[PDB]
Amino acid sequence: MRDVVSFEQPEFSVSRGDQVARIPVIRRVLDGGKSQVSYRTQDGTAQGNRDYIPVEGELLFQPGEAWKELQVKLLELRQVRRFHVQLSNPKFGAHLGQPHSTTIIIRDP
């Protein structure tokens, strides 16, 4: 498989006070062209519009591009809550690698 797109890790941990989660997405074994995947947040115990700002869209990798950073905004209100991000719908010859979903763990300062 070429143009393999994944999250770098199955979990990332952030502080609620950071205002943003910075989530790396990599593309490996480049064939030389563009690739696209879709991405979307999904609630866990962290909930959209309470704990974080939901987002969905497309990640278009131009030729040569090996990674992206997703930035999901965090909201302020011992406490731990999780949301998820999922990759789907590979286009232009792209494939999903492992992990293609990830969990963002929001912790109190």
Image: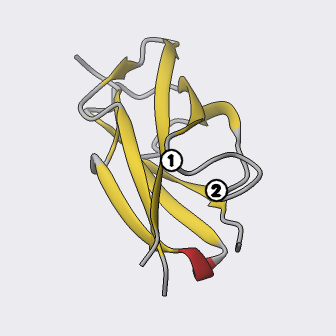
Tell me the number on the disc at residue 45: 1
Q: Position of residue 72 (x, y in %)?
A: 64, 56
Q: Is residue 40 left or right of residue 6?
A: right
Q: Nearer the viewer, residue 79 or 6?
A: 79
| Residue plotted at (68% across, 34% down) | 56
Q: Quadrant of residue 6?
A: top left
The one nearer the camera, 5 or 70, is 70
Where residue 37 appears, x then y in whole percent? 53, 24
Q: Nearer the viewer, mark 2 or mark 1?
A: 1
Residue at mark 2 to residue at mark 1: CA–CA distance: 16 Å
- Determine crowd level at label 2: few under 14, some 14-19, many 20+ residues with C-alpha closer than 10 A: some
The residue sitting at the bottom extreme is 109
Q: Residue 55 location in percent, x, y? A: 70, 41
Check disc 1 and give the amino acid type: Thr
Q: From what the image shows, is residue 44 above or below residue 81?
A: above
Residue at 43% from the left image edge and 12% from the top image edge: 93
Q: Residue at 55% of width from left, 64% of height from top?
A: 21
Residue type at mark 2 is Val
Camera-side residue of 17 and 66 = 17
The residue singled out by tag 2 in the image is 72
Of pointers 2 and 1, the one earlier in the residue sequence: 1
